[PDB]
Length: 228
Length: 65
Ligand SMILES: [Ca+2]
Ligand SMILES: [Ca+2]
Ligand SMILES: [Ca+2]
Ligand SMILES: [Ca+2]
Image (tube, rainbow over all chains, first blue to last red; front, side):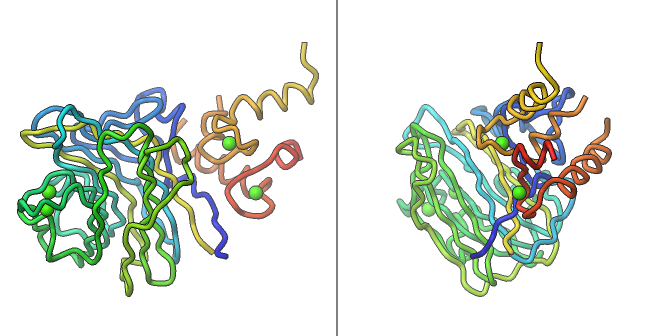
């Protein structure tokens, strides 16, 4: 309770992640995202990068859960800019919000590495809802827009970080495996959104961006489950 | 040389990349050979016919029918 159905059409993973032509089956990629056989480098550790990967079609699931496995790797104790996980009405292939479009209709879960407001509260994981009219407040790390958040250093961890994001009965729950160990099921609570309203149909997505400082933002897998 | 039942289990095992002894739609997409829409049609068909509990996975018995 509830039961999960794996949804291949809204998922990707290795070890044959890309097709013979380097495309990701069922997903569109844009900007400087680089797909490969065992991961997508959504944005590489170069200056001023943007990249994204979005499902080609909308999903229509009443309740759902995504498990996203990733690394954010950089030479410095401080990195930028971060990675975003999305469920939104429209594809946001390119834009200023962690590589994706602003003014989305849905939810973004932002893994924000860089402390733009100097509040000494990064890296942070920030959940921001939007109806299509709100501009992401990048300068303040979306602080006044955040439905819920946690502080979690997802950078430079020895094992892949995992985010399990569950939309169930109008609530959104984010659990995080911090990647300190190779135990892939070691999740800890991050944040929960009550009265979470999202579109009935929408694309899933992942995106990343860099600035003057730059990490490699790598996604090893994005696994989507329908909950019934 | 491998028998019919042996090549079938070999095909199943060779495409079970995560080792969970089940095939999912992504694994099945690698086990053909086309457009993504044709691929979807084929995979949806296999799941419809094989996946008895509708969890998105098929075991060897279901695959082998
Ligand atoms: Ca920031
Ligand atoms: Ca901050
Ligand atoms: Ca498998
Ligand atoms: Ca099954």
